Image (tube, coloured by chain):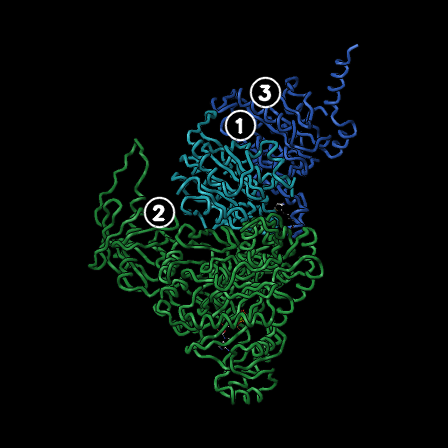
Chain colours: A green, B blue, C cyan
Amino acid sequence: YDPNEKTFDKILVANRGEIACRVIRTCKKMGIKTVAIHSDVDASSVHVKMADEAVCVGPAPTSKSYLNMDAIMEAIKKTRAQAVHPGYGFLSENKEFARCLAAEDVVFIGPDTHAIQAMGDKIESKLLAKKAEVNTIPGFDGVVKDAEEAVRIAREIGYPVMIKASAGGGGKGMRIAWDDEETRDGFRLSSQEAASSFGDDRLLIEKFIDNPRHIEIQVLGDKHGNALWLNERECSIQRRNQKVVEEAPSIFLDAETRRAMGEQAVALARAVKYSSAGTVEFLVDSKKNFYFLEMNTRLQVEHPVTECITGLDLVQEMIRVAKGYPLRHKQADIRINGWAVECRVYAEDPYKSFGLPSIGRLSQYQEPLHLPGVRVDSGIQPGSDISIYYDPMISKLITYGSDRTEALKRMADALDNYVIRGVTHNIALLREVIINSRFVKGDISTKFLSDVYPDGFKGHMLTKSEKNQLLAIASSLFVAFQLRAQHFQENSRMPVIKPDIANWELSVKLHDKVHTVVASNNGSVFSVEVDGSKLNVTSTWNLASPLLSVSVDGTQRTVQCLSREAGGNMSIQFLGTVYKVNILTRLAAELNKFMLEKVTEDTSSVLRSPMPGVVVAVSVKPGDAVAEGQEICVIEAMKMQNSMTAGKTGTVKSVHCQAGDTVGEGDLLVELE
Amino acid sequence: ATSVNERIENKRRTALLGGGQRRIDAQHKRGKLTARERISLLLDPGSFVESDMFVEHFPGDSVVTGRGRINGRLVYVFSQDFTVFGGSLSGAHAQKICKIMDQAITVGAPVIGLNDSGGAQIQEGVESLAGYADIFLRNVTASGVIPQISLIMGPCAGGAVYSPALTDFTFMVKDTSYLFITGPDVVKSVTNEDVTQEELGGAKTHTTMSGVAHRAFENDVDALCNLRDFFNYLPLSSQDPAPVRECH
Amino acid sequence: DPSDRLVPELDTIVPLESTKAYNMVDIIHSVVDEREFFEIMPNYAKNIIVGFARMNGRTVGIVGNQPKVASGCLDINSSVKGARFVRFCDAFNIPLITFVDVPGFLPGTAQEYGGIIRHGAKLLYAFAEATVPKVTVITRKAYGGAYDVMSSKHLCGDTNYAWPTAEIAVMGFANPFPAAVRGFVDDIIQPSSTRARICCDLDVLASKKVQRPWRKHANIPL
Ligand SMILES: Nc1ncnc2c1ncn2[C@@H]1O[C@H](COP(=O)(O)OP(=O)(O)OP(=O)(O)O)[C@@H](O)[C@H]1O
Ligand SMILES: *C(=O)CCCC[C@@H]1SC[C@@H]2NC(=O)N[C@@H]21
Ligand SMILES: [Mg+2]
């Protein structure tokens, strides 16, 4: 971080989200003017405000805003930007972008083009790697044209079969085939889907490694032929073939095999003449055998975690390399310093298919920056909007420590002290993963989520002690609210005679069980009797702060009160999971037995229009099954656009509401089963 | 030579004639009188005292305000005539009306308002809304203190139709008076129905089904005569008992 | 709940283009103490929102427009719903907070035949008669006499504020500056400071006394 060295004066970050914020931060920290591009929707995002100047580039969709080649080119033209930084995704690995940038004097901060089209395609990358004397997954080189050829290949490449669409990526077009019939039908369906997904229409058949570990090697190279490998990364916890939880040092690896993998990655990088930061991904089996699989010729999403152990700012190194300066670190200089673990906080519901994207606006957002050893990379601020146009990822949370246990404990504390209200996130899944016994022990594969939760994610299965603690905390909170309700100001006309109730006897309904609780208050200390068990809860009892810190029997806990109703309903986020409880007094509980249960499920197979209007836009297509709280269509009425949500989970039979069709109140909008 | 006297005479003659002989004549072919003629018919002969006749925005400011006597009892009146000029209930118009209500509430005498928006530009400056708000505040303040009577003698539209509603009694003139917030053209633009002005806000609509107006009279002279007769019933203020007259 | 808590969520809650709507209940929840709000008539005349909340521990009555429902336009039902709530809050010394996004009155022949004039006058009377402290915040729109309806400065509105997206005009001068230069709004505040500002005002106006002429009772346009 020496400003004396001459460096590019203007850098334009052609990206959005947390990566743009990170690039802007590291450019500001070395004294470089920054330009950030944005769409019309992201006119008030964090990265736009962090930059020195910004220019709108087009409409909401990314196909016309962050992929509008010309618009970015003239955006550079007005601001006379000296360098361009693509981050990851979007235009990071586009050859036409690199060529168009090279047409002018402005330099593209990234790998050279030749490497980009060398590693862009999978078959040629595998052939080069085999020529680069590095281990590769067993298989047949070339493109298989017919299913009979696929089964003939499977005859010798082993019974397990892995079919993968050429090029593309993002966890698409990858399937498992077991039998010959499975091989042929999977090949046929993948060939059919290749045109729809990528259009390359090329497939690869390989040997599927059982219980693999997706290890990653970060490589940094300059234009002088110097290549360095910076430790490793383990990326095993994945759903839909997408990384979720990563660790900087790999607990499986040892010094010798780490050195071997680093040397192989450096040799492969030299064989391609890489001149930036990249990643080489290996699939290490149980027998410490690593096979090369794909090379990302761009900055990695999980790059910050390996910055914690090494202590190096990767983006600064890429900028310096682009300037032309040589590398200031040698292979011996690289060493591991502690442990680091990071997690991806998405805006998705973890209870459906291990995560289903959600939308909404953030009514509350707070990060645990004050906690020890916590770093948050987020392009989100309170009041931000999670739309359907971009990746619904909210943040990246990084925790480092002296060893793995300290890092994991800090990660759990940070997850407990992290506030998101407005959308549905996956913090519960993250906490359950980091506190799982197998993860702590270190035995994890790429099918961790599949076999640990066969049926699916259900939440934190809380034990007897934890259940007693939760019931005690909920009862104490209820009694605290009741006590606060009695604190009025002096009236001097009708003085308030505070009731002298000593013991609150309560009925608490959790899941499908009813518990009897006896709570007593002694100032800031509550004594709770839960079915014979005696608990002692002490706290400051601040009923307005989003985060509440309590001490139950000495054990420190952090809880959140998401919801609270006068009818006794309460939602408590405890140990990362949201639990619904119903607290009543004993008299109210006894009298509740005479209340007849009211059926309200009904059918609701027809969605009557709530307000009269004329439909002008239709967000979905008929026959597309949707869940609750999802966009349907846009109705224009009296110069007002109104958007509704789907009513029932049932499959959409037909979207009756269509553009140009007037739909008055009480008319069917979307037919449901 | 001093031009002050001739300037004063010219100002008085312009205020009396208003917009000219052509404008009063055009008002006459519509079967309606002017503000000053209505005031002369309503009040006792030789009892009207006008206020702020020299205040300009053009003298008069399209409203005639003053005090008079009906059968010997004091009353405060204002009369609107926007056909001559102005076309805006924004500037000194609202100030004059507010001041006349202030005098009435200070003394403790009823207020009679002859509403005739006529040809008024509803697309004028923001001063119109402020004046309307001030007038509404004064009507609410005077409610229950002094009686307030409104006589709609012409087409009243926009936000000005809330001042008559806040008064105690509202009267209309058949075939020449209207009360509506939104014009028929905007109604057709929004609701998409063909409605004429008379059946949207006419006297019959507001006296038979709307329940806004209290009575409808044949024409201006009949309306003013009935207004005098009705005013003879009420007390001058809530501080006074119900009037007692000679009985036979 | 600190009285100076910032609410940065309100900075971008109002869409730039006037053709889009938003939820006023979100603003109300963001501003009030503990995000707790007891709504009155939540399922009737949904184009206006009335309810009880607390600011700095003091009970306040809240009235606002709902641009989601009928573009926030005022009609007979909403006028009657708001008027009685305002009258009750005034009768029992409960301060009033208003959020204004009204584009006008709902046009049509049904509204005229139902007596929209009388019920609009009810709302005007309810806002003008109140002698309790009242604080008004204009979020986006205030058109025509409707702006006069919801406690303009000229109806003895104690303090009036406007967000940078507020726009006051007679008909559909596209900025609040004509209102600011003429004293129609005390200040143009940032949306994130709203709550804080309101609290300060409620601390000042707690000792407000006004004097009005004697009467047995006035004449509501009932
Ligand atoms: N041949 C294979 N054998 C076993 N597992 C595999 C195989 N190919 C892919 N996988 C699994 O699928 C994941 C996806 O790997 P890969 O890098 O090919 O995906 P991608 O969608 O192209 O990635 P990216 O977004 O980084 O370009 C791997 O991490 C691994 O868990
Ligand atoms: C298009 O149909 C024209 C819209 C005019 C209605 C708007 S909104 C409500 C206000 N009341 C009125 O008469 N015009 C304004
Ligand atoms: Mg990959």
Residue drawn at the location 33% of the way across and 51% of the way down:
A549
Please tell me how many numbered marks the rendered image carries: 3
**Helix, strand, or loop for circle 1?**
loop
Q: Is residue C67 above or below residue B123?
A: below
Answer yes or no: do the residues labelled 3 and 2 have beta carbons within 8 Å? no
How far apart are labels 2 and 1 at the CA level? 54 Å
Tag nearer the camera, 2 or 1: 2
* Quarter holding residue A205: bottom right
Circle 3 packing at 10 Å, graded few (<14), some (14-19), many (20+), is few
Q: Chain of mark 1?
A: B
Residue on which disc 1 sits:
B147
* Quarter holding residue B170: top right
How far apart are labels 1 and 3 at the CA level? 17 Å
Label 3 is placed on what type of residue?
Asn
Where is residue C11? Give x, y as percent.
Answer: 53, 46
Residue on which disc 3 sits:
B71
Residue on which disc 2 sits:
A543
Front residue (pair B210, A188):
A188
Front residue (pair A264, A20):
A264
